[PDB]
Image (tube, rainbow over the protein chains, first blue to last red):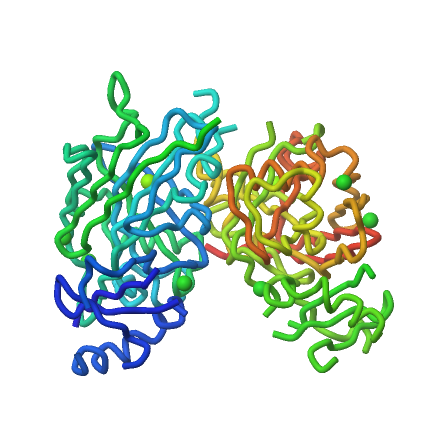
Length: 265
Length: 265
Ligand SMILES: [Cl-]
Ligand SMILES: [Cl-]
Ligand SMILES: [Cl-]
Ligand SMILES: [Cl-]
Ligand SMILES: [Cl-]
Ligand SMILES: [Cl-]
Ligand SMILES: [Mg+2]
Ligand SMILES: [Mg+2]
């Protein structure tokens, strides 16, 4: 029942197995999100290589992208917004703009909204989530705090600053939220390691708190926070460098490989 | 050539005269924006009361809503983002949430993007603007600064916090940006009075500076700043009260009348 839905970089796919995928139309992302609960058994009962096709952002045009700051202890929570045009795919380069010398990474688990809602009650949060995706809240910290009048939208909003995927891991038949363990490496070296059990606000409370002040629609994405190990937390800092490769992994949500390139002056 | 396009509260309309409107389909908002320059002469050459029909937000589902802080001297500029679900119509109530006792008004002129762009050059900015709308960047200042870790997205993002309209005043044949004079009153009393000549960053420079870090699509809205006279700028403050009526006016962009109601505890 937990389907894994991809986008061929519009064309939806589902994972046949953990190594193989198939096109789905023959058998809009936001518009397929809103119809998943009834066709989920259809698609699942009615059930080629993943290394050989190009995979996009699973939700390529979310209505809004909400990101939470300070939702882990090693990194109350602050609601940020990322430009929807920051959205990017699971193998796409992160491009450090000409205007930044302090580009940071932040591995997060995103939920994708499946039914609209406002002042969603905690116990009903699960009914509004279509599923989950791996994500990164890439942030140009020097742009965001040009004198540490913050420019947080600017710092989080450039193209390529919201990598997502490789798939939407659907909620299927779940009556509660799932738990994930996730890691981010750069050139093979461990930078971040988290479990969603360390969230100050769990998935349900995230949906509750965000929707307490922002009305949500199907296709909206919420990044639920990053743990410690970010670039800014060291001396010297460990910000993204030209030629770094970000590798992010979660057992249920797949893997990202994001090459880093600087814009030239 | 400067058409005035409304939305019947989807159904587009054009203003026949300053007192009368007509439906347009027989003769998507974002999708009509992207086709305006070629049908503009069609609609204009091929050219009932306004007090008798309900008028909506002219762009009801913009992809993103950007708002500028500090773009007037009496109020460098800071880029904010409003939730697209804050968008609201020209006669719709502003609803002060249960969680705010400091709801402020900010009359602004918005531009609406008509052609996509990123790192738009100043002299080409006009080619990317479909037109202009009156707007308000309503802000719950106590939510935004819960200890004057800012919650600016929260403070600007509630439903009803981005009134727009009554119409999209199109660019038509203009080779440069136009000038507007605008005012906001509450229960007939003058609060704010501005002219776009006082913008620190003019319309073209707004498009340039915003698009220098955020990629823009057709249907995106930019609020270009508010002048002085906001609630927070007085002792005692002059924040929106239950039963206040906001009246905003610009000669070319029409008028708003927004009743204020508090959510009960
Ligand atoms: Cl989409
Ligand atoms: Cl749960
Ligand atoms: Cl996992
Ligand atoms: Cl729209
Ligand atoms: Cl100009
Ligand atoms: Cl005017
Ligand atoms: Mg974050
Ligand atoms: Mg403003």
